Length: 57
Image 1 (tube, one colour):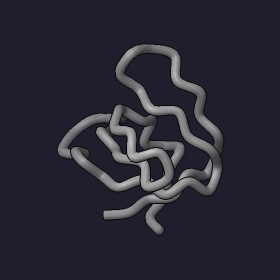
Image 2 (tube, rainbow, N blue to C red; image 1 turned 45 degrees about the vertical axis):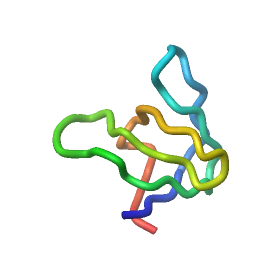
Image 3 (tube, rainbow, N blue to C red; image 1 turned 30 degrees about the vertical axis):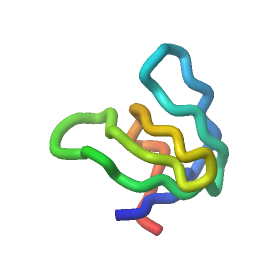
């Protein structure tokens, strides 16, 4: 499922994914939690993102 970033996000660790507002991100894993594993359709990188920064697209 594809979500779209509502805000910019700047990563702070090894495992999260930076992204820009409007970037489209594929869900890799959102089975549970506030942090989701996502895959960017702009960069192709995969990492954890804050779920409250994205909405379905």
